[PDB]
Image (tube, rainbow, N blue to C red; front, side, top):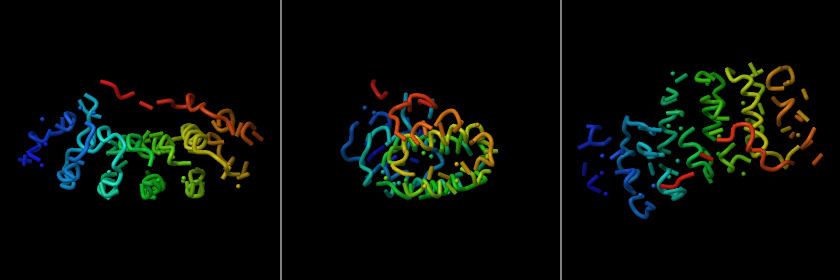
Amino acid sequence: GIILVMRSCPPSQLDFYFQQLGSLISIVKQHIRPHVEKIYGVIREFFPIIKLQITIISVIESISKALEGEFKRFVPETLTFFLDILENDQSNKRIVPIRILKSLVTFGPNLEDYSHLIMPIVVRMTEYSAGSLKKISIITLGRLAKNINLSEMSSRIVQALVRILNNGDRELTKATMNTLSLLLLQLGTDFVVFVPVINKALLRNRIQHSVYDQLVNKLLNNECLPTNIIFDKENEVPERK
């Protein structure tokens, strides 16, 4: 299995270990679970790809292998995945963000906190819409993970949807990513939602909340409403072979 740490580490041999990984969906482990950290706490320039077989080089092999657990193993494995992200994330690299959205929904959800407080950090970066999709799905592949309803952030993620007064480069998609951000993770809450009527100093994030969510939302105002998470953006993508 320790013969596959033994192994010269050119990346040609590593890519046999990046395919040895997919050998072990076979596992479910069991106890290779110190060695997983052993040769990525290493910490190479191959990166958490969807590649060429449904198996990841080499972090999101572990999420799709160990299924969920141990997360006790993935909190230091949760300092050596955001230690990267900090200069791993520009405007172009959208290539580890697709690899941080891909580690996102796989691991979810998930006691995980500086994960739930440094994301935050990657969204709260005002000028970070620059690959548009990237921080759009920071708002699908956050919400899908239901861990974000356990919310402290509501009022800092209210101060991350009018600090953009709609028009950053979302922008009729800040309109749909905020109707996805709120519903599933929603209320058991009032003051987050008497606020928006005011932020109407905007005209896209106002007239996709004025026919989708402020209407399920003229709707949620006296009654909530379940499912309809089979509408906005559906894709929950099963695992079989």
